[PDB]
Length: 50
Length: 100
Image 1 (cartoon, rainbow over the protein chains, first blue to last red):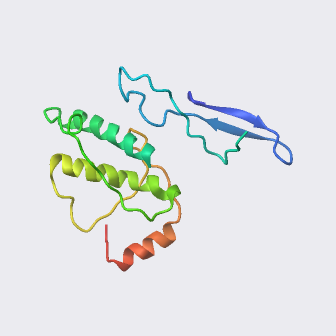
Image 2 (cartoon, rainbow over the protein chains, first blue to last red; image 1 turned 45 degrees about the vertical axis):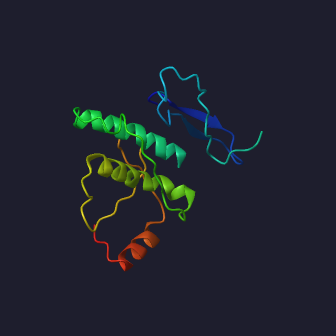
């Protein structure tokens, strides 16, 4: 599990599975050194509204 | 595509300072760009390497080598990741005679 990935238990519909959550910077942070902009996330994996 | 576009803008900046430091094109030169619509968004990252190939091509000004096409995702480092639907892509590409 190199940083930004880790195993995570999930209670699937039958049994459970060690789904590996994955996380990574997706577009460089340095849009401006002075920039105050937030790191908006772009979720994937069949996102629900809740 | 905005993610692939700016991720490619940055890595192209990074690649230019990494390879030809004397040049300052991607680090400072305004560029309008356009990408034709039509492809499904899921494969659109596959086009990002093409995006870089265009940007750097204009950067140096060198024409791209003729009769070749490439597709692949980029993660601000230049590594490529798998893209689906290859059986349809290769046949439709062959009909135009592209060989590379």
